[PDB]
C-alpha cells in the first residue's frame, strides 16, 4: 500500500546520512561541522539570520525534515551562502573559508549528480507534492 | 560582510 512512500523516504534518509558523513569527515569542511560560535564571532548573528552546519543537517535528516534531495541541497546551499555572505575577502583566512564553502557546495552537488537516481529523486519530490494536498 | 573570523 502507501508503505511504498515511507520506503522511499527511508532510503532517501540512508542516502543523505552517507553523503553527509562523507562531507563531515572531509578535512576541508571541518569549519562547517559545528555551528558558528557567537563567543568567537560576536557579529555573526547580526549578518546571518538562518544558521546552518553539517551537524544540524544530520539532526534534520534523523528527524525527517528532508523529504527530497532538493530540500537537503537547500541546506547545503545555505551553509555555503551564509559563509560567502558573512565572510569578507580581506586576508588569506577569509579566502580559505570562502573557497571551502564553494567546495562544500560543489562536492555535495557532484556526489548527488553521480550517485542519485533521477527517477528516485523525482518520486520523492512528487510524493511530497501529493502530501501537500 | 561581517568582520570575519579569527579576530
Image: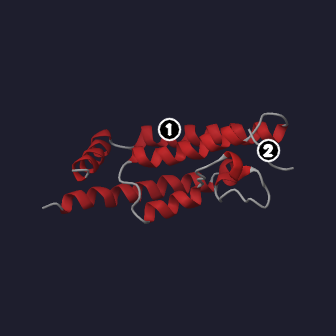
SS under mark 1: helix
Spot occupied by residue A125 in the image (x, y as percentages of width and height): 30, 45
Q: Disc 2 to disc 1, how far (Cα)?
A: 28 Å
SS under mark 2: loop
Q: Chain of mark 1?
A: A
Residue A3 is at least partly visible in this image: yes
Spot occupied by residue A56 in the image (x, y as percentages of width and height): 55, 60
Q: Residue at x 56, y 45 (%)?
A: A78
Q: Residue at x 45, y 49 (%)?
A: A72
In-image side of A115 versus A119 (left or right) = right
In-image side of A66 versus A83 (left or right) = left
Quarter of the image for the N terminus of chain A: give it. Answer: bottom left
Q: Residues within 10 Å of mark 2 (few under 14, many from 20)?
A: many
Q: Is residue A59 above or below residue A127?
A: below
User: Quick one: which residue is furthest to the top in this view?
Assistant: A89
User: Quick one: which residue is furthest to the front in this view?
Assistant: A46
Q: Residue at x 16, y 60 (%)?
A: A2
The residue at which mark 2 appears reads as B4
Residue A100 is at least partly visible in this image: no
Q: Foreground mark, 2 or 1? A: 2
Q: Residue at x 24, y 50 (%)?
A: A127
The residue at which mark 1 appears reads as A110
Spot occupied by residue A44 in the image (x, y as percentages of width and height): 72, 50
Amino acid at each position: 500500500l502507501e508503505e511504498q512512500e515511507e520506503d522511499t523516504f527511508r532510503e532517501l534518509r540512508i542516502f543523505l546520512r552517507n553523503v553527509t558523513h562523507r562531507l563531515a569527515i572531509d578535512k576541508r569542511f571541518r569549519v562547517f561541522t559545528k555551528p558558528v560560535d557567537p563567543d568567537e564571532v560576536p557579529d555573526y548573528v547580526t549578518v546571518i539570520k538562518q544558521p546552518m552546519d553539517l551537524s544540524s543537517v544530520i539532526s534534520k535528516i534523523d528527524l525527517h525534515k528532508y523529504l527530497t534531495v532538493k530540500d537537503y541541497l537547500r541546506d547545503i546551499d545555505l551553509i555555503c551562502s551564509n559563509a560567502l555572505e558573512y565572510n569578507p575577502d580581506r586576508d588569506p583566512g577569509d579566502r580559505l573559508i570562502r573557497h571551502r564553502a564553494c567546495a562544500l557546495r560543489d562536492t555535495a552537488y557532484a556526489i548527488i549528480k553521480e550517485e542519485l537516481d533521477e527517477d528516485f529523486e523525482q518520486l520523492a519530490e512528487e510524493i511530497q507534492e501529493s502530501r501537500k494536498k | 560582510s561581517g568582520r570575519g573570523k579569527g579576530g
